[PDB]
Amino acid sequence: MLPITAADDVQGLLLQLRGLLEQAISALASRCTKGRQLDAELLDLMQVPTFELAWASAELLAAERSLQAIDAGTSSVDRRLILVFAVEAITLVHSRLEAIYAELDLADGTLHAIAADQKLRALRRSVLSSTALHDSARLMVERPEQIGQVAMGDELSMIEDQFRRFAADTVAPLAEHIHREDLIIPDSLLAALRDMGVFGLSIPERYGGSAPDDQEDPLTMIVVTEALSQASLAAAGSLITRPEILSRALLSGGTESQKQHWLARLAVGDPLCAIAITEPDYGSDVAGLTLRGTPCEGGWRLNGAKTWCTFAGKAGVLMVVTRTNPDKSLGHRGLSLLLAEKPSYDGHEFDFRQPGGGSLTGRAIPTIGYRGMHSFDLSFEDFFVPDGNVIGEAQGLGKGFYHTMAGMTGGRMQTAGRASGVMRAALLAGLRYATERKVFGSPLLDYPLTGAKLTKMAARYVASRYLTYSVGRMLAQGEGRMEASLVKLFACRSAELVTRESLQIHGGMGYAEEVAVSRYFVDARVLSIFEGAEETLALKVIGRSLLEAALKAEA
Amino acid sequence: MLPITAADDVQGLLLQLRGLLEQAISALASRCTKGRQLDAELLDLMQVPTFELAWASAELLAAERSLQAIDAGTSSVDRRLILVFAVEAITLVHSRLEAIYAELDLADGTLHAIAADQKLRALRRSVLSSTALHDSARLMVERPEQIGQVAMGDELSMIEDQFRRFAADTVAPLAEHIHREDLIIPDSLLAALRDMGVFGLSIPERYGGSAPDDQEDPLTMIVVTEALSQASLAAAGSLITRPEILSRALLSGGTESQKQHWLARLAVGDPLCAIAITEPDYGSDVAGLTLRGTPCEGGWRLNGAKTWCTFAGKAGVLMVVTRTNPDKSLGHRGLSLLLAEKPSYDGHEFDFRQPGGGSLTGRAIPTIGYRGMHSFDLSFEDFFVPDGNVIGEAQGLGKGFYHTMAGMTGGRMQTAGRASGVMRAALLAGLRYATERKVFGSPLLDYPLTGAKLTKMAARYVASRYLTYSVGRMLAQGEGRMEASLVKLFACRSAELVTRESLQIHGGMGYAEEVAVSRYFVDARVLSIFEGAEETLALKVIGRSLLEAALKAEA
Ligand SMILES: C[C@@H](CC(=O)O)C(=O)SCCNC(=O)CCNC(=O)[C@H](O)C(C)(C)COP(=O)(O)OP(=O)(O)OC[C@H]1O[C@@H](n2cnc3c(N)ncnc32)[C@H](O)[C@@H]1OP(=O)(O)O
Ligand SMILES: C[C@@H](CC(=O)O)C(=O)SCCNC(=O)CCNC(=O)[C@H](O)C(C)(C)COP(=O)(O)OP(=O)(O)OC[C@H]1O[C@@H](n2cnc3c(N)ncnc32)[C@H](O)[C@@H]1OP(=O)(O)O
Ligand SMILES: Cc1cc2nc3c(=O)[nH]c(=O)nc-3n(C[C@H](O)[C@H](O)[C@H](O)COP(=O)(O)OP(=O)(O)OC[C@H]3O[C@@H](n4cnc5c(N)ncnc54)[C@H](O)[C@@H]3O)c2cc1C
Ligand SMILES: Cc1cc2nc3c(=O)[nH]c(=O)nc-3n(C[C@H](O)[C@H](O)[C@H](O)COP(=O)(O)OP(=O)(O)OC[C@H]3O[C@@H](n4cnc5c(N)ncnc54)[C@H](O)[C@@H]3O)c2cc1C
C-alpha cells in the first residue's frame, strides 16, 4: 500500500510547479510583446522556450486532471497509476522549468528548493519504488478491466461495451490483412459501421444524426472512437474523423439548406466525405494555401493540387479549402470552403472527367502505417464547383479559414480518442505477453524492470485518458478550445512512447508484422504529425494562447 | 563562438558525477552480495537501479570520450557539438542519479550541490542557448563534412571516401525498392560488394582476408560498415555482420585446418554465412537453448527449431548453437557450434533434403523494416552435420557458448557502426529538408526550434561516433569487451531518437515510403532489439560487469 499522505503531497508540489510555470509564461509573454501586443517576429525568435512551456503545460495539466478525478468510484488500479504519473510529472515539469528558467534568465532558487524537498524524495521512494511499480503491474494483470475506468454514466458505459464487442468480433479479425495488403476498407465493414451509427455521432438529431440538438457533448464520439481505434486506427477509428471535421464546418458556416441537404446525407455515409486542406507546399500553414478558384457563370473552376487527402478515392464529396480571391495580400481572408463532388472509386488511383471538361485525378501515397483509406495526391484541372456548394454561399466567401479552424478543434479532440485506443491496445498486448513469455526461468512479468515499464506505460495511458475526458467535458460547456490541441499533443506523443515500449517488451516478436504491436507502433507514429503537427500546435495554438491570456490578465 | 572556459567547467562537472555514479555502483554491489559473491536472486531484485546505472554510465562515457578527443585537428563543428552533448549529459546523468540515489536510499546532498552550481547554469545559457544551437545548425549546413570527423588516418579516410562513393552510386538507388517489395538482396549487388572486399574485413591476410595477421583492428570494419549502412542498413551495412561473428568464433575456437578451410572461402562469399543462435523459446537466454544434437556415426543429427535466422535462405553455411549434451542443467556448458551446410535459396521459403534424408526447412518472418536478407523460422529434422564441422572438432564440444560470446563482442561493435551509419543518413536528410522546405515565409532551418532539434540530433550522433571509435581502439588493444556492449546500447537507442526526430522535421513527408527517412525510422527500431536487446545488455553484461568490478576492487 502507498502512504496515506501521497495524494496531498503530490497536489501541493504540483501547485508549486504551476506557480513557477505561470511566472515563466508571463516572463515570456513580456519578451514577445511590442506595444501592448504579441509580435510575430519576437514569437519566432522565442520558439524554444515557447515549445518547452507548451510541453510543461501539457504534462502539468495531465497530472492535475488525473489527480482531481480520484473519487469513491476510482478503481484501485487507477488510484495507483494516477499517483505514479503525478510523481513522474513533478520531475518532468521541474526538468523543463529549469531549462526554461535558464533560457529566460529567471532566478532558479525556488526550483532548487522543490528538487531538494524531502516530500518529493519520499514520493520517489514510495510511489516510484521498484516494489510499488511491480505491485501495480501485478494488480493490472489481475484486473485489466479496471485500467483507465474513467467516470461515465451507465449509458456511455453500455455504448462502450457494445462497440468494444463489435470491434473485437468484426474489426480486429480484419486489421492485419488490411494493413499488410494495403486494402481499401471493405464495403461490408463500411455498411456495418454505418448501421452502428458511426458517421452521425457528430451530427444533430434535427439533421439526421444522433447528437442531441440542444448541446455539444463529444464524450459519445470519444468513447466510440477509442473502442474502434483499439482494433484498427485507420480502418475503424478514423472513419469518425472526416464527418467530425466537415459537420463542424457546416454547422459553423453552412446555410440552413446546406446543413439540411448535406448533414443528413453524411450521417448515413451517402456520400462518404474527405478533407482536402493540405497542399504540396503548405500543411501547417493553412493561411497560405494556394489552390486557385476562379469564378465562372454559376460557380467556380478549381486549378492546382492537394495532397495527403485521406479517403479521397472512396469519398463522394471533398471539403476543399480554395483561394477564391486572387489578391494574396489577404492571407487567410482569401479562402473559402468548397464541396467538390465526385464518383466513388475503390482503387489506388482514379481519373474523373467532368461534363464541362474539368478533371480530378488522384494517386495514393504509400505510407508505413495508417492504412485502409489511402491518402492521395490530387490534381484539379478546371474542376467546376457550383455556387451552391460554397459553404455559406455568398457570405462564406473569404471565411473558409474560420470554418476550417472550427472543424480542427473537433478533429483534434477525436484524435486524442484515437491515440487513447491505440495506447490501450498496445498496453493490453504488453501485459499479456509479459505474463506468458518466460525468460531465465520465470515469466517476464516477474522481473522488476518489466513491472516498472508496464506501470509507467499504463500511468501515461491513464493520465492521457482522464485528461481526454476532462477536455471533452470542457468542450461540452463551450470551453477548452486550446485544450483540445493540448490533449491531442499530449496523447499523440504518449501513443508513440507507449507503443515503442510495448514493442520492446515483446522482443523480436514486436518487430514482426504478424504481431499486432508492430502495427500499433508504425500507426502511432503518424498521430503527432497529422491533424496539427506537434510543433505547430505547441507554438501556434497552445503557446500563442498561453501568452495571449497572460498579456490580457496583466493589461 | 562558445566560451573558452566551457571545457574545464564541463570536465569538472562530469568528474563530480562520475564520483557519485561510482559510489552508487559500490552501494548496489553490496546490496547484491551474498558471501563475497554476486547473487542471482538479489541481482533480479535490484534490476531497476542496475538498468539506470547502466544507462547513466553510457551517457557519461560518451560525453567523457568525446571531450577527451578534442585536439588541434578537431573540426569547428565538432568542438561545438561535443560541448552540446556534454552539457546535456551532465543533466541526463544527474537526473538518473537522483532516481538511483533515492532507490538505494543514499544521501543526495551533493546532487543538490551540482544542480545548483553556477557553472552549470552558465553552461546552459551559453552552450545550450537558442542562439548557440541555431548557430551550430547553420554551421553544419555550410560544412556538412565536418560533422563527426573523428581522427582516422589517411588510409582509413581514403577507405571511407571510396565506400561512400560506392554506397551513394550503387546501393542507395536500390534501397527503396528492396524494402518496399521485400526483395532478396540482388546478386549483382552481392557480387559488387564481394569484389570490394566486404566479406573479408575481419579475416587475417594469412587466412585469405584483408585484415592484419598480428593485430585485431576493428576500425576498418567499422568505417566500411558506417558508409554502407548510410545507404542501406539491411542490404549493405549488415553484410559485414555475419562474417564478423563467424570469423571471430572460428578464430576463437576453430582448429588450424578449419581456419584455413573456412575463412578463405567466407572472405569471398563462397559460401555466404548466417548466424543461427535464437530459438522460439530463447533469445536473450543463450545458455538455455535446446536445439538438440544427437551423436551418430561420423557426426551429429540435429532436431528442433531456430528462429529469426537472418539470411538463412541465401547462406550456404549456418553457424548453429547446438545442445550436444543431454544434461540440460549444464546450461552453457552443454552447447557446441556446428556448421550446417545447405544449398543457397533466394526465396521467402526453402525446403532442403540431404541425400541421407535429413531435413532443413525455412519460412521468412515479415518485418516492419530491416528488409533484404529475410529472417527465418527454421526446422531441423534429423539434419546431419559431420564431426569436422564442429568448431574445434572434438575439443570444441561443450565450448560453443564461449566462442559465441566472443563472436557477439565483434557483432555488437559492428552494430554500433551500423547505428552510426543510419544516424548519419537520418541527420543529413533532416538538414537537407530543413534548408529546402519553407514554412510561414522562411526556410524551416531559419526557425530556432528547428536549429535546436538539428543540433541536438547531431550532438548525439557525434558523441556516439566518438565513443564508437574509442571503443574500437580498445578492442584493438585487447580491451573493451564490456564497452562493446555499452556503445552498442548507446548508439542503437540513439539511432531511434535521431530517426524519430528527422522524420518529425519532414512532417507528413516523413511518413511516406517514397521518402527515405520513413525507412530509416522503421530500420532503426530493430537496433535496440537484436544483437543483444537493450535490457539484456544493460542488466547481464554492462550492469553485471560494473558490479563485479566494484566487488573485486573492494576485496
Ligand atoms: C483529417 C486529418 C488527417 C486524418 O485524420 O486522416 C488531417 O490531418 S486534416 C489537415 C489538418 N490541418 C491542420 O491541422 C492545420 C494546422 N495549422 C493550423 O491550424 C493553423 O494554420 C495554425 C494553427 C498554424 C494557425 O494559423 P495562423 O497563425 O496563420 O492563424 P491565426 O491563429 O493567427 O488566426 C487567423 C484567424 O482565424 C481565427 N481563428 C483562429 N483559430 C480559430 C478557431 N479555432 N475558430 C475560429 N477562428 C479562429 C483567428 O482569430 C484569426 O481571426 P482574425 O484575426 O482574422 O479576425
Ligand atoms: C546476427 C544478429 C542479428 C543481425 O544482425 O541480423 C543477432 O541478433 S544474433 C543473436 C544475438 N544474441 C545475443 O546477443 C545473446 C544475448 N545474450 C547473451 O549474450 C548472454 O546469454 C548473456 C549476456 C545473457 C549472458 O548469459 P549468462 O548470464 O547466462 O552467462 P554468463 O555471463 O554468466 O557467463 C557464462 C560463461 O561464459 C563466459 N563468458 C561470458 N561472456 C564471455 C565472452 N565475451 N567471451 C568469453 N566467455 C564469456 C563467462 O565467463 C562464463 O564462463 P564460465 O564461468 O563458465 O567459465
Ligand atoms: C497519413 C497522413 C494522412 C493525412 N490525412 C490528411 C487529410 O485527410 N486531409 C488534409 O488536408 N491533410 C492530411 N494530412 C496532412 C497533415 O495534416 C499534415 O502533414 C500536417 O498538417 C503537417 O503539415 P506538413 O506535412 O506540410 O509539414 P510542414 O508544415 O511542412 O512542417 C514541417 C515540420 O516543421 C514544423 N513546423 C511547421 N511550422 C513551423 C514553424 N513556423 N516553426 C518551426 N517549426 C515548424 C512542423 O511541426 C513539422 O515538424 C495527412 C498526412 C499524413 C502523413
Ligand atoms: C529482424 C530481426 C533479426 C534478427 N537476426 C538474428 C540472426 O540472424 N540470428 C539469431 O540467432 N538471432 C537473430 N535475432 C534475434 C535477436 O537477437 C533477439 O530477438 C534478441 O536476442 C532478443 O531475444 P527475444 O526476441 O527472444 O526476446 P526475449 O529474450 O524473450 O525478451 C523479451 C524482453 O524482455 C527483456 N528481458 C529479457 N530478459 C530479461 C530479464 N532477465 N529481466 C528483465 N527483462 C528481460 C528483453 O530485453 C526484451 O525486452 C533477430 C531478431 C530480429 C527482430
Image: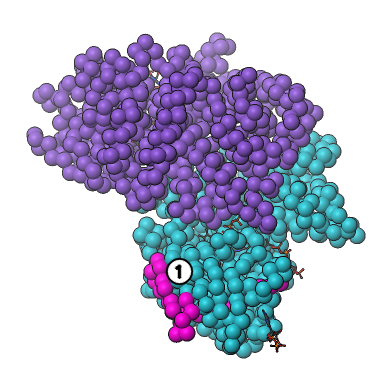
Chain colours: A purple, B cyan
- Callout 1 crowding tier (Cα within 10 Å): few <14, some 14–19, many ≥20: many
Residue at the far left: name it: A356
Q: Position of residue A12 (x, y in %)?
A: 71, 20
Q: Mark 1 lies on which chain?
A: B
Q: Where is residue A448 in the image (x, y as percent from the top left)?
A: 70, 45
Query: Within the image, what quadrant is residue B302 found in?
Result: bottom right
Image point (77%, 53%), residue name = B41
Residue B464 visible in image: no
- Left or right: A148, with B504 as reference point: right
Q: Position of residue A2 (x, y in %)?
A: 74, 29
Closer to the camera in the image, A67 or B382: B382
Residue marked by disc 1: B362
Up-down: is B193 above or below A344?
Answer: below
Q: Position of residue B338 (x, y in %)?
A: 59, 78
Asked if the stretch drawn in magenta spans residue B335, the answer is yes
Q: In which quarter of the image is ligand 4?
A: bottom right
The magenta segment: B332-359
Which quarter shows the N terminus of chain B?
A: top right
Residue at the far right: name it: B555
Up-down: is A430 above or below B222?
Answer: above
Q: Which structural element holds mark 1?
A: strand
Query: Within the image, what quadrant is residue A376 found in?
Result: top left
